[PDB]
Image: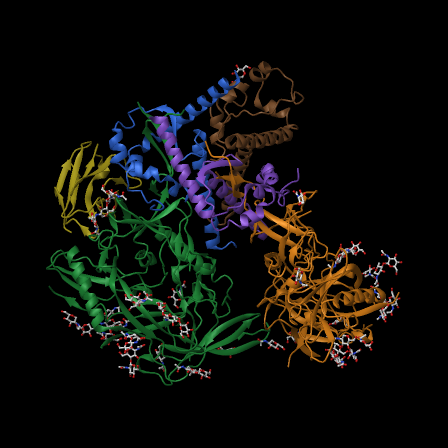
Chain colours: A purple, B blue, C brown, D green, E orange, F yellow
Amino acid sequence: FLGFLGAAGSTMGAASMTLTVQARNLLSLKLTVWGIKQLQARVLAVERYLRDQQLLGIWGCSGKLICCTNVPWNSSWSNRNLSEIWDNMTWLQWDKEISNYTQIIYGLLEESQNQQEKNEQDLLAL
Amino acid sequence: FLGFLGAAGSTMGAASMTLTVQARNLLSLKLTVWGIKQLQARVLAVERYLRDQQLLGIWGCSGKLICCTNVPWNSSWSNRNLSEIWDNMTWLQWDKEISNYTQIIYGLLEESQNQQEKNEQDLLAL
Amino acid sequence: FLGFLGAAGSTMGAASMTLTVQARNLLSLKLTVWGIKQLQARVLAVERYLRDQQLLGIWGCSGKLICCTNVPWNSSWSNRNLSEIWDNMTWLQWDKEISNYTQIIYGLLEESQNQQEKNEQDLLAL
Amino acid sequence: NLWVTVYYGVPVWKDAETTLFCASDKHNVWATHACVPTDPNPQEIHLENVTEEFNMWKNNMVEQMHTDIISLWDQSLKPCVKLTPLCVTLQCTNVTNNITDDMRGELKNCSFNMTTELRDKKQKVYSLFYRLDVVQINNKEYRLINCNTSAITQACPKVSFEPIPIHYCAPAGFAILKCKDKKFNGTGPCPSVSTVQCTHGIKPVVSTQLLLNGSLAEEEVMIRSENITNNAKNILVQFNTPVQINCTRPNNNTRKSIRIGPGQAFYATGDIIGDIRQAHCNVSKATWNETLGKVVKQLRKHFGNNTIIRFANSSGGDLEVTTHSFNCGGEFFYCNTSGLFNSTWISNDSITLPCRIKQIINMWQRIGQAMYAPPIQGVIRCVSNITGLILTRDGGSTNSTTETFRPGGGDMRDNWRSELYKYKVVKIEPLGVAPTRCKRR
Amino acid sequence: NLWVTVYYGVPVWKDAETTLFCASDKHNVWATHACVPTDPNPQEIHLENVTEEFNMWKNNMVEQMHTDIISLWDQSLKPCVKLTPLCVTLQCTNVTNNITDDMRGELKNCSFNMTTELRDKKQKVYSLFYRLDVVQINNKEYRLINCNTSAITQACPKVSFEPIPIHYCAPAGFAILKCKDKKFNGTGPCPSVSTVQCTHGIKPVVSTQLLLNGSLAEEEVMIRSENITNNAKNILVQFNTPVQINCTRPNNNTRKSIRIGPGQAFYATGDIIGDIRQAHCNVSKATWNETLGKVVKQLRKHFGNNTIIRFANSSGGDLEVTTHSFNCGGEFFYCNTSGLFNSTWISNDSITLPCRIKQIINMWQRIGQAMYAPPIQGVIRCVSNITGLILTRDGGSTNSTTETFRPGGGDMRDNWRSELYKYKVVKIEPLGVAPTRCKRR
Amino acid sequence: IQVTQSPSSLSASIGDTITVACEVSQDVGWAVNWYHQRPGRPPYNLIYTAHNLAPGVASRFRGSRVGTYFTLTINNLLPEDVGTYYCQVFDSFAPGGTRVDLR
Ligand SMILES: *[C@@H]1O[C@H](CO)[C@@H](O[C@@H]2O[C@H](CO)[C@@H](O[C@@H]3O[C@H](CO)[C@@H](O)[C@H](O)[C@@H]3O)[C@H](O)[C@H]2NC(C)=O)[C@H](O)[C@H]1NC(C)=O
Ligand SMILES: *[C@@H]1O[C@H](CO)[C@@H](O[C@@H]2O[C@H](CO)[C@@H](O[C@@H]3O[C@H](CO)[C@@H](O)[C@H](O)[C@@H]3O)[C@H](O)[C@H]2NC(C)=O)[C@H](O)[C@H]1NC(C)=O
Ligand SMILES: *[C@@H]1O[C@H](CO)[C@@H](O[C@@H]2O[C@H](CO)[C@@H](O)[C@H](O)[C@H]2NC(C)=O)[C@H](O)[C@H]1NC(C)=O
Ligand SMILES: *[C@@H]1O[C@H](CO)[C@@H](O[C@@H]2O[C@H](CO)[C@@H](O)[C@H](O)[C@H]2NC(C)=O)[C@H](O)[C@H]1NC(C)=O
Ligand SMILES: *[C@@H]1O[C@H](CO)[C@@H](O[C@@H]2O[C@H](CO)[C@@H](O)[C@H](O)[C@H]2NC(C)=O)[C@H](O)[C@H]1NC(C)=O
Ligand SMILES: *[C@@H]1O[C@H](CO)[C@@H](O[C@@H]2O[C@H](CO)[C@@H](O)[C@H](O)[C@H]2NC(C)=O)[C@H](O)[C@H]1NC(C)=O
Ligand SMILES: *[C@@H]1O[C@H](CO)[C@@H](O[C@@H]2O[C@H](CO)[C@@H](O)[C@H](O)[C@H]2NC(C)=O)[C@H](O)[C@H]1NC(C)=O
Ligand SMILES: *[C@@H]1O[C@H](CO)[C@@H](O[C@@H]2O[C@H](CO)[C@@H](O)[C@H](O)[C@H]2NC(C)=O)[C@H](O)[C@H]1NC(C)=O
Ligand SMILES: *[C@@H]1O[C@H](CO)[C@@H](O[C@@H]2O[C@H](CO)[C@@H](O)[C@H](O)[C@H]2NC(C)=O)[C@H](O)[C@H]1NC(C)=O
Ligand SMILES: *[C@@H]1O[C@H](CO)[C@@H](O[C@@H]2O[C@H](CO)[C@@H](O)[C@H](O)[C@H]2NC(C)=O)[C@H](O)[C@H]1NC(C)=O
Ligand SMILES: *[C@@H]1O[C@H](CO)[C@@H](O[C@@H]2O[C@H](CO)[C@@H](O)[C@H](O)[C@H]2NC(C)=O)[C@H](O)[C@H]1NC(C)=O
Ligand SMILES: *[C@@H]1O[C@H](CO)[C@@H](O[C@@H]2O[C@H](CO)[C@@H](O)[C@H](O)[C@H]2NC(C)=O)[C@H](O)[C@H]1NC(C)=O
Ligand SMILES: *[C@@H]1O[C@H](CO)[C@@H](O)[C@H](O)[C@H]1NC(C)=O
Ligand SMILES: *[C@@H]1O[C@H](CO)[C@@H](O)[C@H](O)[C@H]1NC(C)=O
Ligand SMILES: *[C@@H]1O[C@H](CO)[C@@H](O)[C@H](O)[C@H]1NC(C)=O
Ligand SMILES: *[C@@H]1O[C@H](CO)[C@@H](O)[C@H](O)[C@H]1NC(C)=O
Ligand SMILES: *[C@@H]1O[C@H](CO)[C@@H](O)[C@H](O)[C@H]1NC(C)=O
Ligand SMILES: *[C@@H]1O[C@H](CO)[C@@H](O)[C@H](O)[C@H]1NC(C)=O
Ligand SMILES: *[C@@H]1O[C@H](CO)[C@@H](O)[C@H](O)[C@H]1NC(C)=O
Ligand SMILES: *[C@@H]1O[C@H](CO)[C@@H](O)[C@H](O)[C@H]1NC(C)=O
Ligand SMILES: *[C@@H]1O[C@H](CO)[C@@H](O)[C@H](O)[C@H]1NC(C)=O
Ligand SMILES: *[C@@H]1O[C@H](CO)[C@@H](O)[C@H](O)[C@H]1NC(C)=O
Ligand SMILES: *[C@@H]1O[C@H](CO)[C@@H](O)[C@H](O)[C@H]1NC(C)=O
Ligand SMILES: *[C@@H]1O[C@H](CO)[C@@H](O)[C@H](O)[C@H]1NC(C)=O
Ligand SMILES: *[C@@H]1O[C@H](CO)[C@@H](O)[C@H](O)[C@H]1NC(C)=O
Ligand SMILES: *[C@@H]1O[C@H](CO)[C@@H](O)[C@H](O)[C@H]1NC(C)=O
Ligand SMILES: *[C@@H]1O[C@H](CO)[C@@H](O)[C@H](O)[C@H]1NC(C)=O
Ligand SMILES: *[C@@H]1O[C@H](CO)[C@@H](O)[C@H](O)[C@H]1NC(C)=O
Ligand SMILES: *[C@@H]1O[C@H](CO)[C@@H](O)[C@H](O)[C@H]1NC(C)=O
Ligand SMILES: *[C@@H]1O[C@H](CO)[C@@H](O)[C@H](O)[C@H]1NC(C)=O
Ligand SMILES: *[C@@H]1O[C@H](CO)[C@@H](O)[C@H](O)[C@H]1NC(C)=O
Ligand SMILES: *[C@@H]1O[C@H](CO)[C@@H](O)[C@H](O)[C@H]1NC(C)=O
């Protein structure tokens, strides 16, 4: 145990081993300046958490810290070897080098989830 | 792709094919008039989303855009043929002609989910 | 049917039969004193619901009213017989006599869920 | 066999009421700086196959925006000097140097004792007040017309009254439906409905008879009224072409600052450089005649072809309704629009409208509080578009076809509803249940 | 073959701006009671392997907390008596009874007509005003200095200006990064970064030339200044050791309550018991010389070893800048401080600083509002820590190595940036995508 | 718009049920307010919107709409109901009204 963002500089695998400790800290009067700032901060935190939770929910991964999908990884995003990625890299650089391709990945995730769920319904009905 | 409410006038199947685009738009300073109006609007939006997600969760369908269940169609709510419904009808008229029976359907969903979950516990323990 | 907190004094099994009715009531203008009190109450209700939802999500039990885990019962928290607990006790006393061991149980649930998910990752990969 | 299946994100909406926040693309009386920055590229989506009922009158947006504008107007005067010491006996003499025929007695040269910085000490100063601001007491003794009914707070000179377009955006989970029908009269179904995140540029212009700087009709001048039969509901007219209107205040006004207390400054009206003329609004005679011809052509339809349509001036009432009042560059005009609504219709030149100025302005008719608009230095001049009418019909004798229409207004909701006419607020309901052959596991 | 695997809770952060709420461990000006009670044991976490970029000069936190301080200062003033009647003609005489040579003419014994409880009835009362608060009018006639350019509101006597430490805490989903590097030069990467839930005790001390009660540098005196070659950017000096300063006002003042209206009390200055001396501050000569030696040693690095460093006093300007101004037990000082920056450097005793006191205080330079600090009963004595300086370099000819540094200040953001220098606000982004051999079933 | 009423006058004994007609020339929706005027007394509101009772009016009064044909129906007639009945549409009042007196 290291704490909130304890494994920030760790390798990929070690950081993924302790996702919960960072996962549990995203969520936790009069009209005075301090009071209104407190209320704004509270609402901002709750909205950010629900944006993240909804974004997970669209990809059919709600409630799962690590969830797999069915979209292939085009090597244009990153062709690095897995051993180098998961043993000699931190999450910071990883987000640094895929900041631009994030949106298309999210769209592929959404489309794949929708199609897979429709196929599951078709199989369940028959 | 059409966008938010793009398939509002389309048929049932086409609308169901693109549920995500409407799903993803359901969630996305001083004490000035515009500031307080903005804050109230933000809180209203977040609470409406949370209520909808809670209603989905009670029926054991959280995280699933299209979810089926185990309560029969009473056939008094509507006796229309499936082909006519899913090929020559839009969601607007469907909700228009089923609005009064929504509460009992929700209650049936609730009871069915609770009983199914209890049965799953019982068979899981044995 | 009894209503919100209807089976508060009932036995364990009867209370567990009707979790849904207390589950639904957990979530449901100018800068006037009444207005600001209403707004703060609304935000407080939203966050109180979301903390519980997050706690359920971390343990891999989101969307399930009853969820089983892989945390053994230490028998030091309570060694009482199952028949006595589930037929001759109310939830209030049960929470009364485990008020101190709650945090360690929550931590065990969190760690057990995390390891369980990563174990699944290995099998889904291989 | 059959079973029900729950759906998330279905395109289903219901009519609902909600709070709308502003978005907009020097300080302003409307806090546009408090608006969230709108997206440079608005998203608009066409909803084919959709037929939605619309109704400007039962629309909440007009009432909500009336409330919003009143709130902004009230808020913009809270950090402004209160002119309670101005309620002092005045000694006013008519200004009669370099004045024209129409300027006899419209301006008064009033001198009064006023509190200086030092409380015990006093000072005699003079100011120029228009005849409509001062009332005689029975040279002569005058007082500000407000003094026996209200207390004024001077509008802060640095805030601009110019209208800035502002977009009213619904929160998440709500949508705004924009009626794309070009022949939509405002009631009944709108076959072409397109949704947008929020409204186009709405300028909250403050006018009574002629709607300035508004949105034009796409194809033809249209007539929109709740019950045309009822000779009381105002007839909202929207022009398909703009009628340019020019007008200015020829006086070379000077703003003289008078300190009436600690950090409190009252901006008076100094001597005018040069001759003193009349503020007057210009409208092209031929353009106005053509627009009136189009209006009467489209109006005959609602009634009959053989009926006589006659435009007469305002019958009477307070100055705001009788005339055409509107703020121009920080000054409030009151224009005597009698030369416009004068023609009678049967099946280069400009019209000069003599306007009158007022400084003590009481908009929204608030009981107890009114405004003193500070004078604007220099010669103010604004070029606006006449984009609409507000006509009130007069009940006939049930014996003649001489329908008489007169300008109306006063109710600013009528002025504003010509801009929110094509919009509607709906509540997204994304939970749907439908029968399908699926079964849970 | 590879596939994408979503991850929740990854330790990824981006630089971002957000609202920070207060937390802290008699009513006070900063309303620290409104701050949430901080945890008795802060959660401080060390993030090694991490190198994060830092920049105090473009940090939001300084601007945000400056805005917070101004808002608090304004809000603590609203429910306080408004001293508009005090702006009345004064009859002031020299206070020459039991005064020293340096006190000649600094006090004024002003007597004035003041309104009483009964509005019609007037009243004559006298009070003592410092020479910097009253200006002659051309015994003689005087007035309060800001009665022709601002409104004076008395600070409520029962609220204390003493700085209570406040912690700025970010909301959930945000983190505060603390640069643990003891050699952080004020910008660039910080090799040893650590996160904390929120900041340590920050005292919003008000000072211009010397930093009072600040946080010490851990190892050595540090010189931090964006673009040090720019001879207009203030140089933030931080001391590794504290220089004790003793400030006192020997006068035994009496607070005389003068009722100027219904429930409104203006707290005046009565007769002083005993001799009247000059309020002064004391700094140890040897300690100050040693600190200056350390500062000049650390300052030769950025300019060269052979250069001459000379400290002259602050150049012309307003009183708050030309002097070392601060608050001491409810009173605002203005200290000479020419004996501090007095020497030149080439490769038991105390320094008495004659301070002047002011009651009319206009902090933040707001247009129209000024504050009247009520007098403090008894002799006030303050023991503070000189923990920093605001040095402004001066340009020179190309033939001179005599770099002259003078005390600066005024911009309180420079006073406060020395306390938020090692902190930063980041936004947690817990969603990550990584390639794994797993494919959803 | 011309508005007509019929019959011009009528006499009913105690307790009878009587109705009065108010015909409109054009579509007026339901805007046909009714007013009763006791002899020597100012008129007061009976029915607004053509079917809604004014405050203080007994439930024994009823109004209805048949297209452009409008009726005010009175049950169990009582002595205080004597007087004249007027129907208003916008700015138009029926000429003469309808006089109701005891038999
Ligand atoms: C309808 O829209 C037109 C066009 O925006 C408005 O005309 C503008 O009115 C403002 C009023 O002050 C003029 O601003 C002035 O501009 C001069 C230019 O030198 C400047 O020196 C003044 O200090 C002042 O800012 C502006 O020039 C004028 N024209 C344009 C193109 O903006 C008109 O006022 C609007 N209608 C109403 C009723 O406000
Ligand atoms: C820097 O910090 C020091 C200590 O935190 C400040 O000295 C303190 O100053 C306050 C008032 O300014 C003193 O409180 C007063 O004490 C007297 C005598 O006990 C009492 O009669 C008053 O009612 C009030 O409580 C406090 O004693 C004093 N602390 C000491 C001397 O250790 C100093 O003012 C700060 N520098 C600033 C704010 O510039
Ligand atoms: C006022 O009317 C003038 C025209 O007299 C507008 O100027 C242009 O008018 C043409 C004619 O349709 C439009 O195509 C242009 O788009 C207008 N210019 C701009 C910049 O939009 C002018 O915009 C009108 N001002 C208003 C409505 O405020
Ligand atoms: C005149 O105005 C009345 C105002 O109510 C209109 O009446 C309503 O019309 C709507 C039309 O959809 C109906 O749904 C309502 O039930 C009507 N109610 C009432 C109180 O009448 C009327 O239609 C208008 N008609 C004309 C000729 O303009
Ligand atoms: C409005 O129009 C009138 C005339 O219709 C203008 O008045 C004339 O202005 C010119 C200068 O531009 C003078 O030389 C004339 O003596 C004026 N009177 C007449 C009868 O021509 C007036 O300037 C216009 N105002 C505007 C455009 O703001
Ligand atoms: C209102 O003023 C505008 C100018 O501010 C007038 O437009 C001018 O019209 C004349 C004659 O047609 C042209 O020669 C100018 O080039 C125009 N100036 C422009 C367009 O900037 C307009 O005619 C005036 N309208 C009225 C009714 O007086
Ligand atoms: C509408 O026009 C009529 C006539 O065109 C105006 O009647 C005049 O009113 C003034 C009072 O200001 C009288 O001195 C005149 O004798 C009237 N002329 C008549 C009766 O022919 C009337 O004032 C106008 N109403 C407005 C402009 O609101
Ligand atoms: C508004 O305009 C009308 C018409 O120009 C004015 O009515 C004229 O008033 C003068 C005296 O002010 C009379 O001599 C005329 O006989 C009136 N009629 C006409 C056709 O000129 C009216 O006075 C103006 N002002 C107001 C306030 O209505
Ligand atoms: C600051 O130091 C000066 C001396 O450098 C102190 O002045 C002396 O004060 C004592 C009283 O404690 C007197 O008896 C001496 O006569 C004073 N000497 C002078 C004026 O030369 C002064 O008190 C100190 N101030 C503090 C400690 O606040
Ligand atoms: C400022 O005042 C404090 C206390 O009044 C001084 O601290 C005292 O210093 C003397 C030496 O002169 C010691 O004997 C005492 O034991 C100290 N007492 C405390 C409580 O610290 C301090 O020296 C003064 N500093 C200056 C520069 O005048
Ligand atoms: C910095 O030091 C200089 C010189 O010691 C001060 O200059 C003196 O200013 C006063 C004005 O109060 C004059 O009466 C003296 O004649 C000046 N002495 C000179 C020029 O040698 C200067 O005032 C000091 N700075 C401050 C802010 O006090
Ligand atoms: C700040 O202090 C310095 C030195 O203590 C003052 O400069 C002296 O002022 C006196 C008063 O006129 C002169 O007689 C001296 O010649 C000045 N120089 C020196 C070296 O003593 C300066 O005036 C003070 N600043 C003020 C009072 O604002
Ligand atoms: C920091 O780096 C060292 C060497 O690269 C490594 O052994 C250590 O595990 C890293 N820190 C963490 C928390 O992983
Ligand atoms: C509208 O209806 C027509 C005919 O029923 C259909 O072909 C068309 O696809 C519909 N619109 C959309 C957007 O599906
Ligand atoms: C209360 O207790 C009795 C016996 O202890 C039990 O029979 C009864 O069901 C309980 N009440 C409820 C509401 O269950
Ligand atoms: C108004 O009267 C003052 C004297 O009280 C005079 O100085 C000024 O010129 C007058 N202004 C006019 C006549 O416009
Ligand atoms: C001054 O103007 C008034 C109108 O307000 C008028 O009644 C009076 O006769 C005028 N006096 C003159 C011109 O001497
Ligand atoms: C100001 O007061 C004096 C005092 O008598 C008076 O003579 C003078 O007329 C006053 N000036 C006004 C009322 O303008
Ligand atoms: C104010 O004075 C005017 C005349 O100057 C009068 O007509 C009006 O009724 C007065 N209002 C009051 C006394 O409320
Ligand atoms: C507007 O058009 C609809 C079309 O059905 C019609 O019913 C309605 O009466 C029209 N309204 C007006 C004011 O003409
Ligand atoms: C108005 O007067 C000023 C002098 O105060 C002059 O500079 C300016 O040019 C004048 N404006 C006009 C339009 O004559
Ligand atoms: C406007 O047009 C009508 C058309 O009949 C004409 O009678 C009238 O003289 C015209 N007015 C003008 C051109 O000013
Ligand atoms: C209105 O028209 C009549 C004739 O049609 C004319 O005599 C009168 O002057 C006009 N009014 C104006 C131009 O104000
Ligand atoms: C009174 O005090 C002033 C200080 O502003 C001084 O200039 C003046 O010489 C003093 N006069 C006497 C007589 O003491
Ligand atoms: C100030 O003057 C008053 C008389 O107006 C006197 O009573 C008081 O003692 C004086 N205070 C001094 C000289 O300090
Ligand atoms: C108060 O007013 C009286 C009235 O004349 C005056 O004599 C006295 O000097 C005033 N007191 C002051 C200005 O302090
Ligand atoms: C206020 O009075 C001071 C006295 O010196 C003067 O310098 C300043 O200009 C005045 N401010 C004004 C008149 O606005
Ligand atoms: C601070 O240190 C960094 C380390 O790379 C350097 O780039 C920067 O110039 C330094 N800033 C100074 C010395 O002001
Ligand atoms: C001042 O410095 C001393 C160390 O000499 C320290 O004990 C004291 O707490 C400091 N006072 C502050 C930081 O207010
Ligand atoms: C100040 O004066 C009061 C009497 O008013 C006295 O009790 C106190 O001791 C004095 N303070 C000093 C430091 O002499
Ligand atoms: C400061 O100390 C240094 C070295 O101890 C000495 O050379 C210098 O003269 C001293 N200056 C003062 C003002 O004490
Ligand atoms: C500044 O330093 C010089 C040289 O030591 C000295 O003569 C002068 O008095 C000093 N200024 C002061 C102490 O104010």
Return the residue nearer the eye: C15 or E432: E432
Which quadrant holds the N terminus of chain D? top left
Residue D400, image x, y percentages: 12, 59
Toward the right, the furthest residue is: E348
- The answer to whether one can see residue A92 in this image is yes
Please tell me whether residue A58 is drawn above or below residue D404 in the rendered image: above
Residue D429, image x, y percentages: 37, 39
Please tell me whether residue E239 is drawn above or below residue F12 in the rendered image: below
Residue D254, image x, y percentages: 44, 79
Quadrant of picture, ligand 10: bottom right
Return the residue nearer the eye: B52 or B29: B52
Please tell me whether residue C95 is drawn above or below residue E84 in the rendered image: above
Q: Where is residue A82, by image quadrant?
A: top right
**Apparent side of residue D221 relative to residue C94 in the rendered image (left or right):** left
**Apparent side of residue E49 relative to residue C59 in the rendered image (left or right):** right
Which quadrant holds the C terminus of chain D? top left
Q: Where is residue F30, by image quadrant?
A: top left
